Amino acid sequence: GIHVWHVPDLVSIFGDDAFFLFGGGTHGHPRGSRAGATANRVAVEAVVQARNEGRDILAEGREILEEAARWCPELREAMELWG
Amino acid sequence: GIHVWHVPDLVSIFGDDAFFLFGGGTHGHPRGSRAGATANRVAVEAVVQARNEGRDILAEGREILEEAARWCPELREAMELWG
Ligand SMILES: O=C(O)[C@@](O)(COP(=O)(O)O)[C@H](O)[C@H](O)COP(=O)(O)O
Ligand SMILES: O=C(O)[C@@](O)(COP(=O)(O)O)[C@H](O)[C@H](O)COP(=O)(O)O
Image 1: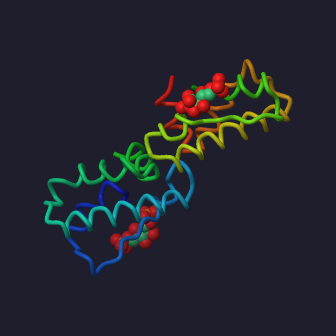
Image 2: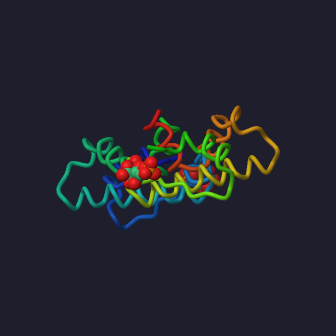
């Protein structure tokens, strides 16, 4: 039962050599599966980029996700729906 | 100085044989011009189609635009920002 909000913690644990499966976190998006997949893809790619830039993921996950939703609506709707 | 909110009034006054120019209503979108041009395009087609459906425009413009924004992310931002 993972969604966009769990992306920063997941990247902290598993690094880059792992699979993240969003069963209900993709199809549960308020605008279908295409938006849900884009939201998760944007969330992961944004958190990884910040980690590669030296930011502290565990502490700045919320800020990274907000900054990415600031330019991606699909992630914005995903976050405001869950958690 | 016309934005998405004025589309129900513009379509009612002018009909379908006219040009609508969104100069500052396209580039003033909180996410650029390509996002702004989509919100203007979706708003017009939603109002025009709902007029071909027989629904009243001058009274149900707000509702029509809200149903359009429910599935268009670009239109939702434009309606939130202006008015
Ligand atoms: O069957 C399910 O629920 C899932 O498809 C999750 O889909 P959602 O993402 O929609 O919950 C997973 O296969 C199980 O959770 C496996 O968990 P484990 O890896 O512990 O076996
Ligand atoms: O200069 C401007 O304001 C515009 O570029 C509109 O920009 P916005 O769309 O940002 O207002 C138009 O040329 C004038 O409004 C013309 O108005 P008229 O058609 O009455 O000459």
